[PDB]
Amino acid sequence: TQNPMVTGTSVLGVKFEGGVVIAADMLGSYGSLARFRNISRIMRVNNSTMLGASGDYADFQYLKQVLGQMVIDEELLGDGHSYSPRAIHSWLTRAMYSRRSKMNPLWNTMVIGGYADGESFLGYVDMLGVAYEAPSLATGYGAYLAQPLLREVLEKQPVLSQTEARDLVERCMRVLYYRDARSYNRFQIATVTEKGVEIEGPLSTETNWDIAHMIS
Amino acid sequence: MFRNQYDNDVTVWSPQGRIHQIEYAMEAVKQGSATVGLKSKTHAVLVALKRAQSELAAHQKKILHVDNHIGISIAGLTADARLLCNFMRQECLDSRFVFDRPLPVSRLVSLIGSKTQIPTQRYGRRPYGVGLLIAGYDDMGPHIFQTCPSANYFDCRAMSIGARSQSARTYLERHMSEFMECNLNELVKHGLRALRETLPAEQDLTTKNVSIGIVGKDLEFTIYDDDDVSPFLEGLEERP
C-alpha cells in the first residue's frame, strides 16, 4: 500500500490488573469524508489475544484474513498449543517489517492486547516494523492526545483495576473526540481477561460544550 | 530363487496391499545401535549406545542438538539423520524467528512426517533409512517421539529403536508405571537399565559407548558425553 485510502484513526490500549482493554472508534474515513461509519477496527485474534488497528482498513482486513486463518489452522491440530499474544505480536512484527523491506508497506498501526499465563500483554506494531510493548498504547493522534492522560495515570498508579482502566479509556476517547478531526462519536471497547475476549460496543462519548457560550 | 516382482521401487503396491520398499526401510533402523528415550513429568531423557570403527576411532555420535528444547537421537542411516537434523534445526530457527517462541515438539514431528512421506510415494527416491527418537520440552510438558521410515510418527511414554531393542521395550513397558514420578537421576538410570539390557552378556555400559541427552523444564537440551556420563553410570547396579 503506497497510498492509504480508507483509514482508521487512533487505537488505544492499557493494561489493567487482570487484562488489557483497547478501544477504537468505528469510523473509516476516506480523506476527510466520514464515509464508513460502522466498521469494527478491533479484531478478536483468539481466546487470549485481541487486536485493534489504525491506518488503511483494507490492509487490516488482509491481516484479519491471514491471522484468522492462522488461528484456525492452529486450532485444527488440537495439540494444546495456542499462539500467545507475544507470538501474534512477533509474527505481526515480522509481517510488517517484511512488507516494509519490499517497499510495499501495509499502511497500518496496530495495538495487540492480550492476556496469557496470568500476565497481560500490550503490543504496538506499525508499518515500518517498530515494535515494543508498554503499559499504555495509543496510535495516530492518540499518541499526542491520549497517551499523556494514560501515562500520567500509569505514573501515579502503575496497577489499574478494570473499572479504572475502562473509565480512563472512555475519558481519552472523549478527548480524542474533542480534538481529533478524524475521530467519531461511536466506538468499540474490547477487553481480554481470563474470561476471554469480549468486544463491547457501539459506545458513545458524553459531550460537553459549555465553552461554546464563553465567547463574547 | 523367490524373486519379487513388487519390491523394486517405492511407488509399487504389492497385490497383498503392501509397499515393500517402505517395509524394507523400516528395518534400516534395526541396522542402528539401540537408543532408549523416556520421559518423566518434568524431563525427557534420550540414552543411546554408540559404537566405534576401531579402538582408535572415536564413537559415532547419535544424540544431536536440534534446538534448546528439542534434541533427537538416531538409529539407521546417519546420512539421512543429517538431512533430518538440518531440516529440523531450520524449522526450529524459523519459528523462533517468526513467533519468538520454541516449537511445539509435536508440530516439528508432524512436519518431519510430512517431509518423509514424500519419498514414500514419488518415483526414483528412497524412504529415509533412519528412525529418530525425539526428546523435547514445551508448554505441554516433556515429549518423547518416535519417527519411522514409514513416515509414521508415534507419541510415546517411552520407546526404544535400534538393533535388539526389544529387550529395552520389555524393560520399559514393565517399568513405565513409575517414570512420571521419577526425579532426573532415577529417570536416567531407568534409561540406562533399558539400554544395558540391549547388550550381550560380556558387554557393559562404559563412558565411551554411552551418550545421554536430557531436556527438561529448567534445563536446556544438553548432551552428556564421555566424562559427563560418569555421574549417571556410577550409581547403577551390577548386571543381573
Image (cartoon, rainbow, N blue to C red):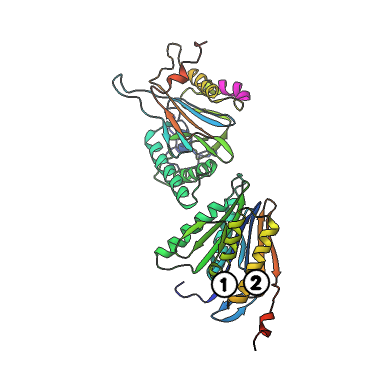
At a point 40% along the width and 63% down the height, the residue shown is A101
Q: Which disc number belongs to residue A174?
A: 2
Q: Which disc number belongs to residue A8?
A: 1
* Disc 1 with disc 2 on a shared chain: yes
Q: Which disc number belongs to residue A62?
A: none
Residue A187 x %, y %: 66, 70
Residue B82 x %, y %: 38, 38
Q: Quadrant of residue B231?
A: top left
- Give the tally of numbered discs: 2
Give B16 or B44, whichever is nearer the viewer. Answer: B44
Residue B69 x %, y %: 49, 38
Which circle's residue, 1 or 2, is located before the other in the chain?
A: 1
Say what amino acid the circle numbered 2 marks.
Answer: Arg
Residue B201 x %, y %: 46, 11
Say what amino acid the circle numbered 1 marks.
Answer: Gly
Task: For label 2, count other residues whose C-alpha is less than 10 Å away and answer few (under 14), some (14-19) or many (20+).
Answer: many
Please report, as a chain letter, where disc 2 is located.
A
Q: Seen in the image, is B182 located left or right of residue B11?
A: right
Q: Which residues are magenta?
A: B171-178
